[PDB]
Length: 357
Image 1: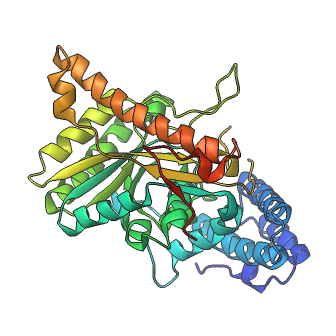
Image 2: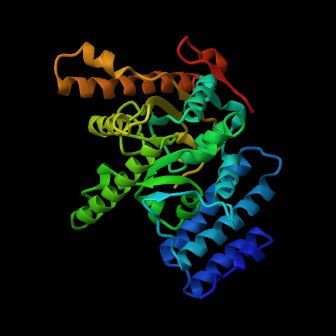
């Protein structure tokens, strides 16, 4: 069994669309995957053309041709994710593939980074051998790429070496897998969906145990940069007001992360991180060109929280809530800069915004 390379011979939208139909009729694409490709093509095309980019036609055809080639390759021979997955960069550079694919969807012109200088401080801690965990919200299946693209110029180390805790659809759906192959990951089934199919819960636990043992081993070696969203899912708009805010954190996931970092025999840090990009690829399909925001702020002192609270349970919830409140402060600044149309004027004493592209 060899890989079919027909999508690479495509030279137009018509040939690209016919190639989907031709591969489907030849039985090489299940109907759901063929439909998802059509949807992906149309939505991506519209978003890039809608953006006004002078090179939209070329960009769409190029990026979609490669994407469809790589998706088909995964349908033919599905990648299996190791507990810890290192980004594949050779012989096909899946990291660059994913960067290039998402780049045209971000309106850099209206995108913002909060507290850039702190990402440099994060690099200096990693240079010292410390471990750093970014405690973040999560908005789209493309978060890792969006994070990486916003920091690619100023902090390429972070952009390429961050290890994302991720799992579920992005590691299973062939439309998403080629993107994930190009990222460093710790593969974990979310608590959120753990019970969706009860017959599979034990299998998921066992897999999460392997991944978490591997993550602890990595932390023992030091210099790890890990991203995790303790809400365990993507943010959703308020059902009443329609307003988007970071989803509440699972305080136990936070506490587990803090404990691992404390018991790694290596100095570690948890920083609150906010990301704003739901418009680009929103959760329940839809793709749009839009500005994005990323911000980090200083670590919360667990000691101070422990010193001002009355018992263990209250301390754990207060610590998670302090991280959440920082993420939400930062997220509000990004929101104010972007949908609030304030740009850099949204800056506050806690969040200094910049556009370093």
